[PDB]
Image (cartoon, coloured by chain):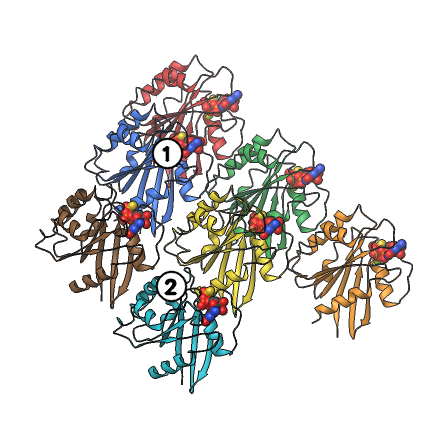
Chain colours: A orange, B yellow, C cyan, D brown, E green, F blue, G red
Amino acid sequence: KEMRILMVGLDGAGKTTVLYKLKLGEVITTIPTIGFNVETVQYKNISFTVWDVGGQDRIRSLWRHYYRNTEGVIFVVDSNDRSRIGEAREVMQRMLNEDELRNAAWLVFANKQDLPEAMSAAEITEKLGLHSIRNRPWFIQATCATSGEGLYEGLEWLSNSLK
Amino acid sequence: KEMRILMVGLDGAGKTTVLYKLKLGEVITTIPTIGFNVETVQYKNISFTVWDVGGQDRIRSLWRHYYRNTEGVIFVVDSNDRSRIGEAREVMQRMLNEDELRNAAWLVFANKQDLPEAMSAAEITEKLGLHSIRNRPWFIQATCATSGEGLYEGLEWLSNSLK
Amino acid sequence: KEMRILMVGLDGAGKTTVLYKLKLGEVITTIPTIGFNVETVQYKNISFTVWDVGGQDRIRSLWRHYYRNTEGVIFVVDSNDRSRIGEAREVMQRMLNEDELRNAAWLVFANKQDLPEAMSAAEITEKLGLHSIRNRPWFIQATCATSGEGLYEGLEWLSNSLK
Amino acid sequence: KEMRILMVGLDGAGKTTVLYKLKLGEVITTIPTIGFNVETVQYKNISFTVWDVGGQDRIRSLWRHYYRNTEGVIFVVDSNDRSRIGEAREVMQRMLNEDELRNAAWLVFANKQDLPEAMSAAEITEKLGLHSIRNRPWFIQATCATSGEGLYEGLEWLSNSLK
Amino acid sequence: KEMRILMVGLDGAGKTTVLYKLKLGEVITTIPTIGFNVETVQYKNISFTVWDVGGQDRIRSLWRHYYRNTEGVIFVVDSNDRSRIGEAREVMQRMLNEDELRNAAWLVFANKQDLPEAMSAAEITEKLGLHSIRNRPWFIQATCATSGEGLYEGLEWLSNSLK
Amino acid sequence: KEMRILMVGLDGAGKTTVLYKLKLGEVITTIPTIGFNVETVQYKNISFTVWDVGGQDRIRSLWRHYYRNTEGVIFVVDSNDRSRIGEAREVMQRMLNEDELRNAAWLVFANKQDLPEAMSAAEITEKLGLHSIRNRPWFIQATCATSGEGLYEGLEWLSNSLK
Amino acid sequence: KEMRILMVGLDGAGKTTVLYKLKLGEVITTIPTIGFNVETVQYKNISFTVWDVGGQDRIRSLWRHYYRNTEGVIFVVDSNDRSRIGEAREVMQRMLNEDELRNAAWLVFANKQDLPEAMSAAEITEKLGLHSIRNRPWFIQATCATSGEGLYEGLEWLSNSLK
Ligand SMILES: Nc1nc2c(ncn2[C@@H]2O[C@H](COP(=O)(O)OP(=O)(O)OP(O)(O)=S)[C@@H](O)[C@H]2O)c(=O)[nH]1
Ligand SMILES: Nc1nc2c(ncn2[C@@H]2O[C@H](COP(=O)(O)OP(=O)(O)OP(O)(O)=S)[C@@H](O)[C@H]2O)c(=O)[nH]1
Ligand SMILES: Nc1nc2c(ncn2[C@@H]2O[C@H](COP(=O)(O)OP(=O)(O)OP(O)(O)=S)[C@@H](O)[C@H]2O)c(=O)[nH]1
Ligand SMILES: Nc1nc2c(ncn2[C@@H]2O[C@H](COP(=O)(O)OP(=O)(O)OP(O)(O)=S)[C@@H](O)[C@H]2O)c(=O)[nH]1
Ligand SMILES: Nc1nc2c(ncn2[C@@H]2O[C@H](COP(=O)(O)OP(=O)(O)OP(O)(O)=S)[C@@H](O)[C@H]2O)c(=O)[nH]1
Ligand SMILES: Nc1nc2c(ncn2[C@@H]2O[C@H](COP(=O)(O)OP(=O)(O)OP(O)(O)=S)[C@@H](O)[C@H]2O)c(=O)[nH]1
Ligand SMILES: Nc1nc2c(ncn2[C@@H]2O[C@H](COP(=O)(O)OP(=O)(O)OP(O)(O)=S)[C@@H](O)[C@H]2O)c(=O)[nH]1
Ligand SMILES: [Mg+2]
Ligand SMILES: [Mg+2]
Ligand SMILES: [Mg+2]
Ligand SMILES: [Mg+2]
Ligand SMILES: [Mg+2]
Ligand SMILES: [Mg+2]
Ligand SMILES: [Mg+2]
């Protein structure tokens, strides 16, 4: 009936694009997210309330204001960006150790799969150290926010962890 | 209705893998256990509370904090490691002489039986000097935490020593 | 109205098979009994609560936990196994000297009579030294748990020692 | 209701094996007894408290600490060891002259009768000079601690000298 | 639930950087620590209260004000600085002899491992004389405060010595 | 319930190593013992309080401060050091004639048996003139403090002389 | 718990430097000691109260005011000063004959060992006639107050003569 979500990731990942592809159905032009966007999207008789936030180094320290009462998390990672996959691992291993996100479900959108140099979801699952997760449910999906592929299959998995 | 367990052993044995094969049912990737893990698993209307600890030489001296109120012990030994079977014997003969574990039940998981060079449970029973045990109930089971074999047959024996 | 029973014996005897031939009516496939099974069976307006236990050498030392409040005992002996009839005699003469089983009724299921090499109930009565019993009522019945023969004639005798 | 016993003898006799055949029912592996073992065993509504001690030449001088308040003594002699039957005679004639064991009952376990070269209980009764005993009740029984033969027939005789 | 920590070391080690890498997650620019910094960081449902202090020769004499009620100590040593490893040994052997830190747990951050000329944790364990510690638990971890490596594995070990 | 011990010997013997192998279970690096170390170790429901002291010629004259109220003595002798076995004999024959140690139990740890040139416990028993002891109980055990062999068999013998 | 000490010696030896290396941990600049300095230093749960005095020829006659109630003495000798080793011998042989220092423990700090021309502790032990001491415990340690070497090993020996 209701669910709260927090979309996060590094800069350039695709968070805003994913959100406004789910909410509107169209690919909008984007500006860097200094503040935050919040939007409700309905699916399977469930109303997800997604909070997209900034990924710039200066806003990554303000994500803590949103950890509270968060039932799911969506970590978006740019697959073409193979040089920052270590920074994302640091961020995610730091945010998995926070106690406010202790029960949160973990979903990972490996975005930008339409690009030729994109890296597979298994290569990302290995590079991010996702099998090391033990206190938490987790899942990884390959997406293309510009085409909508894999986006409605993530909200479908998040439904498993309802209530 | 309840029971407390302490899983111990040398490094590389299989303690964490056993615990999260009982708790989750899947084989997780692992990191060395510097601290401790604690997990409750239900079976036969009994809720075992297992404490997995480190086996590095530096943490083997911190096991004493957990001996108290411990009703069962699970000593995991790597069978393929035939060069450290003497060190495990030292550790176990030292920990059998402690007075806090005076009534504790003893179970021995001879793990890594899937490997070709693995050593039989009787060869381990002879090398560990288990028949020398007289103040304590004891039992040895051959396992394969990656496949789950022999794991639910140890919790089954630990039930004999309930209450 | 009620009665408590303890089924015991060596390994391979037929305890589990007897129990789940009385309770279900079918011959189940079996695994070695590491722990214990407990089942209530009704007959002649009496509800027998049978506790089947392991016979492996390592579990024969845990039978003492069950001697208390036990009103009848059922010693199952494999008749085809003519090489272990001395070990069973040792076990039974040891367990007849325990003071918790001081008033318990003794029944002996000489099982596996369907086999050609099976030994008669009188040969077993002589080999087990059953006439030497003087502080206790006793009885010996020839059975075939696979066919149910002689099983309902043992519960019938146990009724004699009700209340 | 209660009784105190002191099991003694030379090294290699079978004291520890006898004790943990009476207490557990199984034949344990053994280490030389440097200190002492103490165990309570129930039989015929009597709780014997047996103290098994070392037989090495260096511990034979520490037996005096246990003579006090001792109501029965069990001298175990290896029958196969026909070369040390004189040393045992010396030890026993010395310990029969002590005034703390003035009323103690004497029992003699001629152990290791399963061996082919074993010597009869009458040959031992002659070699040990047991008929020379006049201030004391005495008895000699032929045993086999590995099989339990003759062990429960000694505790049965010790009951004669209760209270 | 709570724990008090004292981070100390020589000048240039990395104490402030470690503290504000644990607390904020970012590498801050630094000024010499004339006074003291104090910050609470949460991890594993535990709230560590860390006190970072100066290492200049003039402030090393004011550390005594903080020894009291200190449950853990974190000695940070610059590995690249191979010319001052003797001065750190002097400081640490002096501060191990103080009676206010009598029960304190010892952790050693061998920092600046990202530098090519860095010295291994075992070379430091030998140069600092850490095996000579006998009245105290101790542990040594290799770190890189600029990248966060090895920092959350020290707070994990400090949890072993809780309460 | 309690017992007081004094570990003594020449320099290089293994006293400190033995003590902190019993207390911690690990082989620590060592410095010459100028003062004294004191540690309590529990075993068999007994709490031995061991006082390890220096063996340098200058501290051998300060052992007298500890003779009082000493219930056991542990003389450690280096077996590889076959050139100082006469000096140890002098020291031990001098300290056996003191009246404060009149009732003390004597134990001798012939240490460093892992070395190839080590001398047997009987050769040491002959060289030290241990059979000449008549006013005192005594015992000699062969050890290897680095491996723990023979160490828990000495505390086991010291229990014989309790209270 | 408490102990009183008197540090003495010739001029230029290192008394003040030793005292304020023990008390503060730093090497202070110094002025000739016309009067006296007094400082308490804690170590091994003992609070030594050290009195450093002048060594000028005019103050060497005022040391008598401090001999009373003195439990230990620390004679500091400059090793580089090989021309005044006879004057120190005179002073020490005079102060050993005083009856107020009749039970005092003797410690000798052979300081300034960092200098190349320094003389060994055995050469000093021979030149000072220390083996001639018979009514007193004594000890000699080689130091370097500028580096702290050998200073905490003297207070460690002084603990032997506590109470
Ligand atoms: N070619 C391609 N571009 C994508 C894809 N997904 C997202 N993008 C594009 O990549 C750019 C970055 O996406 P954007 O949503 O603006 O970043 P962000 O996640 O919000 O992070 P920021 O707000 O801090 S800059 C955008 O131009 C967006 O259109 C994809 O699947 N393929
Ligand atoms: N091939 C094989 N590997 C096994 C088996 N059981 C456990 N392991 C593997 O052996 C490795 C060590 O197991 P692990 O559980 O991490 O050690 P530990 O007992 O926790 O000890 P540590 O935490 O101090 S490193 C792991 O890679 C694990 O997957 C087995 O039965 N077969
Ligand atoms: N041919 C034949 N097999 C029998 C008979 N009674 C029991 N068994 C068989 O003998 C085997 C052993 O019986 P089982 O009940 O499993 O042993 P147990 O008494 O439980 O002892 P355990 O659990 O310690 S292995 C089984 O395969 C069982 O089916 C019989 O009358 N005839
Ligand atoms: N073959 C055979 N061995 C026996 C018998 N009784 C005891 N033993 C064996 O003889 C050996 C010595 O028995 P043990 O109990 O250990 O000596 P002890 O009486 O305790 O004396 P010790 O402790 O000073 S070494 C053991 O290996 C034991 O198993 C027997 O009846 N037959
Ligand atoms: N290259 C590199 N620099 C590091 C590392 N860890 C810390 N530092 C850097 O070394 C410098 C000293 O660290 P800093 O934290 O300021 O010293 P301090 O421990 O606080 O001691 P002080 O305050 O008395 S000056 C800083 O410029 C810091 O950024 C590292 O792992 N690699
Ligand atoms: N190879 C070997 N070394 C041993 C053994 N037992 C003790 N040692 C080693 O011999 C050395 C001396 O032992 P140590 O305990 O320091 O002397 P001590 O008895 O305390 O006497 P001291 O303090 O006056 S120097 C140490 O390096 C120790 O590790 C052994 O069994 N084998
Ligand atoms: N190079 C070197 N100098 C030392 C050492 N120990 C002490 N000193 C130095 O020698 C000088 C004399 O030491 P000091 O403590 O002032 O003399 P004193 O013992 O107090 O005697 P006084 O007060 O009557 S002048 C000082 O400059 C001191 O720093 C050492 O180990 N090496
Ligand atoms: Mg955005
Ligand atoms: Mg682990
Ligand atoms: Mg069964
Ligand atoms: Mg024995
Ligand atoms: Mg700083
Ligand atoms: Mg020592
Ligand atoms: Mg001065």
Residue F70 percent location from the top left of the image = 27, 41
In this rendering, position of residue B6 left or right of residue C83: right
**Left or right of residue D43: residue E22:** right
Q: In the rendered structure, which amino acid carries the disc numbered 1?
A: Asn
- According to the picture, the residue beneath numbered tag 2 turns out to be C82
Identify the residue at the far top of this view.
G83
**Circle 1 — which element?**
strand
Depicted A6 relative to depicted G9: above or below: below
* CB at disc 1 and ligand 6 closer than 8 Å: yes
Instruction: State the residue position of label 1.
Output: F111
Q: Please say if the residues under marks 1 and 2 sit with CB atoms less than 8 Å apart.
A: no
| Number of the front mark, 1 or 2 | 2
Q: Position of residue G158 (x, y in %)?
A: 37, 32
Which residue shows up at 46% across the image and 28% down it? G150
Q: Quadrant of the N terminus of chain G?
A: top left
Q: Secondary structure at mark 2?
A: loop
Of the pair D47 and C149, the residue shown nearer to us: C149
Disc 1 with disc 2 on a shared chain: no
Chain of the residue that carries numbered disc 2 in the rendered image = C
The three-letter code of the residue at mark 2 reads Arg
For ligand 3, tell me if the residue under mark 2 lies within 8 Å. Answer: no
Q: Residues within 10 Å of mark 1 (few under 14, many from 20)?
A: many
- Is residue E101 visible in the rendered image? The answer is no
Residue A44 is at least partly visible in this image:
yes
Structural distance between the alpha carbons of marks 1 and 2:
55 Å
